[PDB]
Amino acid sequence: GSSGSSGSGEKPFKCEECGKGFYTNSQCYSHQRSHSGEKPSGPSSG
Ligand SMILES: [Zn+2]
């Protein structure tokens, strides 16, 4: 709704976990990864 102790208002692409800010979808996801640890790695591993 509103904020004060923050600068980045709104962005075209932000994280769903915390709410980070991004400009390109690809980027948004990249970070989103961090929000994952207890998971198996098959075709790709962090
Ligand atoms: Zn996040």
Image: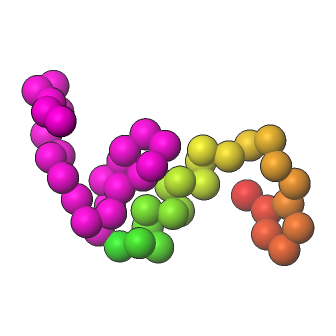
- What is the count of numbered marks? 0
Quarter that holds the C terminus: bottom right
Whether residue 30 is situated above or below residue 20 in the rendered picture:
below
Q: Is residue 10 magenta?
A: yes
Quarter that holds the N terminus: top left
The quarter holding residue 7 reads top left
Where's residue 31, x and y in %?
Answer: 50, 55
Q: Residue at x 87, y 54 (%)?
A: 40
Where's residue 2, x and y in %?
Answer: 14, 33
Q: Which residues are magenta?
A: 1-23
In the image, 2 versus 27, the foreground residue is 2
Q: Is residue 4 magenta?
A: yes
Whether residue 45 is situated above or below residue 6 in the rendered picture:
below
Q: Taken as a whole, is the magenta stretch helix, strand or loop? A: loop
Q: Residue at x 17, y 46 (%)?
A: 8
Where's residue 11, x and y in %?
Answer: 22, 59
Whether residue 5 is situated above or below residue 14 in the rendered picture:
above
Residue farthest along the top direction in this orientation: 5
Q: Residue at x 45, y 49 (%)?
A: 16
Q: Residue at x 41, y 72 (%)?
A: 25
Where's residue 23, x and y in %?
Answer: 29, 68
Q: Tell whether 7 sits left or right of 46.
A: left
Colour mode of the rendering = rainbow
